[PDB]
Image 1 (tube, helix red, strand yellow):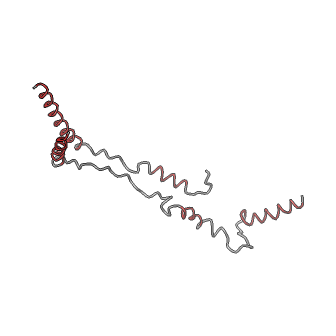
Image 2 (image 1 turned 90 degrees about the vertical axis):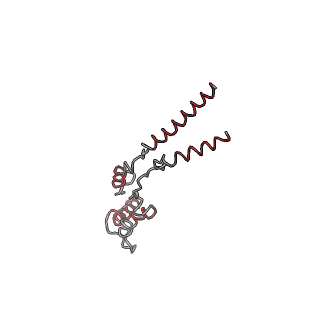
Amino acid sequence: QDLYLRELKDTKLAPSTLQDAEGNVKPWNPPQKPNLPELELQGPEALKAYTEQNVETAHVAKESEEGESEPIEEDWLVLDDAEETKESH
Amino acid sequence: SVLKNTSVIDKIESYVKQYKPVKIDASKQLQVIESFEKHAMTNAKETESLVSKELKD
């Protein structure tokens, strides 16, 4: 149909100008290529953790806590304390 | 694949695979365990022998 074919033409070659050709758009002043492709590509990381989300900051798992291998001082006091607690058993 | 122009899914997977060991485990209990075991076992053996002797008496 002419109304279909003409619509397809005006909506395809112009769609070519918008997307399929890097001619941006004459009717609209700011091209989306200088707006979306790189800066708004940081919009994904603007919503994400910037230079940190894609990066995934290095955080190595640490060691758990222990008694510093100290039986010279902790063992005797622990024994006395446990025996004192045993006085009401 | 759902992200056609991610251009970072390669990088993200690279970091993921290269971050297979973020760090190590910490099984540093190798002499503290021995000393705790020695103290506990000697004390418990003394307790058990004392209990048996009390039973006999």
